[PDB]
Image (cartoon, rainbow, N blue to C red):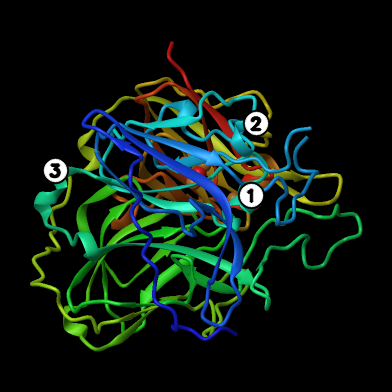
């Protein structure tokens, strides 16, 4: 296997605007097929990248900054990854659309799966409205990320490399003196399988392919043999002996991580998907499912000279391998101090979400289920509805709802709601057999409130097997057509995604 910790961690450059005034910031990003070396000992890898980069450029904006991004497709007309033609039914093979994950975004700028476009916008999906996306950023400072969201192609386009970080800075938070600038570093974690010739491997069929299956065939999960951070296999980062802020983004298709430091040191979590937690939380380890973000401080002050591995204990299709996927990256505390560490790790970060006293307009009960197709494949479904079925999740703008998510399946699903961030209420175990047999919900234990990590704002939430998860969301400020889905991309594409109409009656 590839030698761990021989390549320095890339830090994506921050994107520069094409045009910028005090009223408007205008960006252009072009999707390009390019080649990049992912490891010292590999031939360069063919990839799809925003501005030809993997990950894409980091975009930095201020809260309320009036931002526009013209996301353009200049990709080849044929994919290099295996397309399953059976999962969706002239129309180009390669379709793309950029979704700003966590963006408080008007619906036609949200990257609707059917708002896709081919090269130079030559063909467009039935929900396409505009070339230049509008991000008003009227929302909390937070770690967002952008990625492809095209109908039936998301797992492939993202795996190809179409991911990048987007950071909203709220000037009100500068007073907290969190590590900033060089000491504030995104970590986009993506697992990959890479061939000896350096080409990406993505399976064209399940491991034991029934002759019933089409070819290629979608698979229900993907687990990469190797872990990359910021587009390099098992990299090292030289750090100064002081506090750093890391924006930890899980940009992987399926894989969930459970992260810790191999010296037993702590993380300080300061933020979740929707922004700063009310209070900082000291943690030894944390779970990170696809699309989840952890805003953390790591204090290297007392660890000068040391090599510390960011370790992973979560398996993917099996137990972790100590030599491979148990490793993420390596910090080397050997960079001389550029100046005094004037950063802080404050306890008091933000207003509590519980300060809000909104009326519960509606309680939605939603089940995570599915069926089997003509080929014997699992088709994962939200409420046993297909994507194309008439919309059922129709919250009213400006109203608050409780969603009760029932998971009678064998695994966890990271459920993502577009537009909004929500509060986690509780989780409660139930009798799976009883529910499967009769549709009756019989709890086998008391409700458990969220851990401190989940006492802030979330947008992607782990709904564990055999539990009912309750969340509360205020739907707004925009009305329109959005989506909610499982963020396991292999699930999302077949067919664990539903329209969400935020209505203005
Ligand atoms: Cu997403
Ligand atoms: Cu999203
Ligand atoms: Cu799922
Ligand atoms: Cu999405
Ligand atoms: O998403």
| Residue hosting label 2 | 122
The residue lying toward the viewer, choosing from 161 and 446, is: 161
Q: Which mark is residue 491?
A: 1
For numbered disc 3, what is the local secondary structure? helix
The residue lying toward the viewer, choosing from 430 and 275, is: 275
Please tell me whether mark 3 or mark 2 is closer to you in this view.
2
Q: CA distance from mark 3 to mark 2?
A: 43 Å
Residue 384 pos. (x, y %)? 67, 37
For numbered disc 1, what is the local secondary structure? helix
137 vs 173, left or right, is right
Quarter location, residue 351: top left
Comes first in the chain, label 1 or label 2:
2
8 vs 157, left or right, is left
Quarter location, residue 213: bottom right
Label 3 packing within 10 angstroms: few (<14), some (14-19), many (20+): few
Residue 488 visible in image: no
For numbered disc 2, what is the local secondary structure? loop
Label 2 CB less than 8 angstroms from ligand 4: no
Residue 203 pos. (x, y %)? 73, 63
280 vs 426, left or right, is left
- Furthest toward the front, the residue is 18
Q: Residue at x 54, y 47 (%)?
A: 31
The residue lying toward the viewer, choosing from 281 and 117, is: 117
| Residue hosting label 3 | 172
- Furthest toward the bottom, the residue is 305
């Amino acid at each position: 296997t590839l030698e761990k910790f021989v390549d320095a961690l890339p830090i994506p450059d921050t994107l520069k605007p094409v045009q910028q005034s005090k009223e408007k910031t205008y960006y252009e990003v072009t999707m390009e097929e390019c080649t990049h070396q992912l490891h010292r000992d590999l031939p360069p890898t063919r990839l799809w990248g925003y501005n030809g980069l993997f990950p894409g450029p980091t975009i930095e904006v201020k809260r309320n900054e009036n931002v526009y991004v013209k996301w353009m497709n200049n990709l080849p007309s044929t994919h290099f990854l295996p397309i399953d033609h059976t999962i969706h039914h002239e129309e180009p093979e390669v379709k793309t659309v950029v979704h700003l994950h966590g963006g408080v975004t008007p619906d036609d700028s949200d990257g609707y799966p059917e708002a896709w476009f081919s090269k130079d916008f030559e063909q467009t999906g039935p929900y396409f409205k505009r070339e230049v996306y509008h991000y008003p950023n009227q929302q909390r400072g937070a770690i967002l990320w952008y990625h492809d969201h095209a109908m039936a192609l998301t797992r492939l386009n993202v795996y190809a490399g179409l991911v990048g970080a987007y950071i909203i800075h709220d000037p009100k938070e500068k007073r907290l003196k969190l590590p900033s600038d060089e000491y504030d570093v995104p970590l986009l974690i993506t697992d990959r399988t890479i061939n000896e010739d350096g080409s990406l491997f993505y399976p064209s069929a399940p491991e034991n392919p029934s002759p019933s299956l089409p070819n290629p065939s979608i698979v229900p999960a993907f687990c990469g043999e190797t872990i990359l951070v910021n587009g390099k296999v098992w990299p090292y980062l030289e750090v100064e002996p002081r506090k750093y802020r890391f924006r930890v983004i899980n940009a992987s298709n399926t894989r969930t991580y459970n992260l810790s430091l191999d010296n037993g040191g702590d993380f300080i979590q300061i933020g979740s998907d929707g922004g700063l937690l009310p209070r900082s939380v000291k943690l030894n380890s944390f779970s990170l499912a696809p699309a989840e973000r952890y805003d953390i401080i790591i204090d290297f002050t007392a660890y000068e000279g040391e090599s510390i591995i960011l370790a992973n204990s979560a398996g993917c299709g099996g137990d972790v391998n100590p030599e491979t996927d148990a490793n993420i990256m390596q910090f080397r505390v050997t960079k001389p101090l550029a100046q005094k560490d004037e950063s802080r790790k404050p306890k008091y970060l933000a207003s509590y979400p519980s300060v809000q006293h909104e009326r519960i307009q509606n309680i939605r009960t939603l089940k995570l289920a599915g069926t089997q197709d003509e080929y014997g494949r699992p088709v994962l479904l939200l409420n046993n509805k297909r994507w194309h079925d008439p919309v059922t999740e129709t919250p009213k703008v400006g109203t608050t709802e409780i969603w009760s998510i029932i998971n009678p399946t064998r695994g966890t699903h990271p459920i993502h709601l577009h537009l909004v961030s929500f509060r986690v209420l509780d989780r409660r175990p139930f009798d799976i057999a009883r529910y499967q047999e009769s549709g009756e919900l019989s709890y086998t234990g008391p409700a458990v409130p969220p851990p401190p990590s989940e006492k802030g704002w979330k947008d992607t939430i782990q709904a564990h097997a055999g539990e009912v998860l309750r969340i509360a969301a205020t739907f707004g400020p925009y009305s329109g057509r959005y989506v909610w889905h499982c963020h396991i991309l292999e699930h999302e594409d077949y067919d664990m995604m539903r329209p969400m109409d935020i209505t203005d009656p």
